[PDB]
Length: 110
Length: 98
Length: 109
Length: 114
Image 1: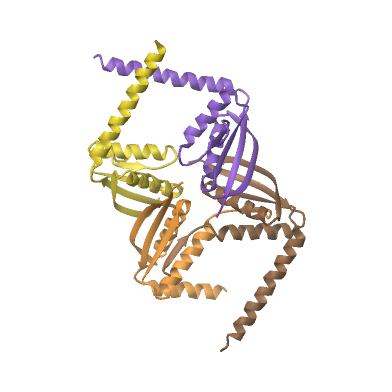
Image 2: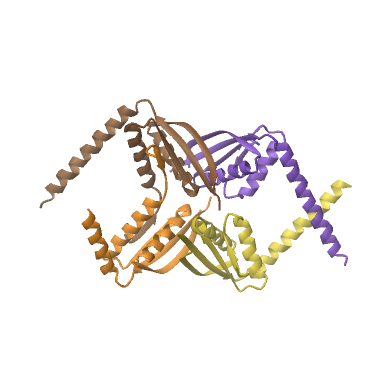
């Protein structure tokens, strides 16, 4: 299973696969292959629609297939315009809240 | 079990595969197979069944989202080569059995 | 015209009709069950039967089989006045089948 | 708009989060938790309860279905209570979550001072 292939399934959440896809595009991957089998095909669409709602990715290709019956979808997404700028502002905002929670937790303990 | 009703999608995929075949046979150059939310899976399997029967080829697949959000898939299928010959053979076998 | 929208409306009606026929055809209780993503439609099938005042829910259980597959099982029995309401639907379904048959022959023009 | 002991399973959260919320609410005094969902999320509410049943944490006290307006919207509601040995199995899960939190904090401060 390649690094740029995210398998959407029940051993995870839609929020986790969105985060993994964002991290893979930010961490060198030019394109991410978002795939799912059978009843999870809709959930793979929800993962990509969330990335599109956040204006982070653009869909490059969608294919359906049947593998060894089990049906399969595969959506290939690449970085959208302003991905780096919108990912780093979200990282800055997530660290600001992670430190403020730590600082107030330490202060509450003292 | 006579008193057990199993609710499922098997009779739904066969109906929509049949509907799609009839529209292609009745003049339509392309059929837009779409579904919302949890029905996206059945729409994909409906197209895979049509591809398995060598009836259609996928020309385009798009996804969209409307306002819980509602996700939508849209698969555009066209006639494959030898559709008429396989549609007439499927009709002959269904009329023979009826 | 060239757009096929795949959905569950009609499939819920088939199982609503099947459940009604099985209760009318001797069965005291019908077990309405479904797996995974069809659990929602199985619940809607029973809610449709409840609005028609045809069944009453006797028991609902959930279970898990080997990803894992979840299962619901709703046991419905006849409601009071089911026979009186089923006979009015059968009579009305026959009035329409004779009308469609007579219309088919009258369309010989 | 809902009571404290009512968990609404939906798209604003994961099944893992609703399982944890239900466990936390039962451990923090609540005698019963109402696990409910609407329409296409009804199956996901069933998976949340089945996960709690696999962990032998809850027992199902009641399941009801109903219909409300938005077309009509169908709803499931599962009432769960503590199973026997819930406290002993929840305390082992709490103990296991602190062990991993202290192992990560101790290791990440060790790595920062190498």
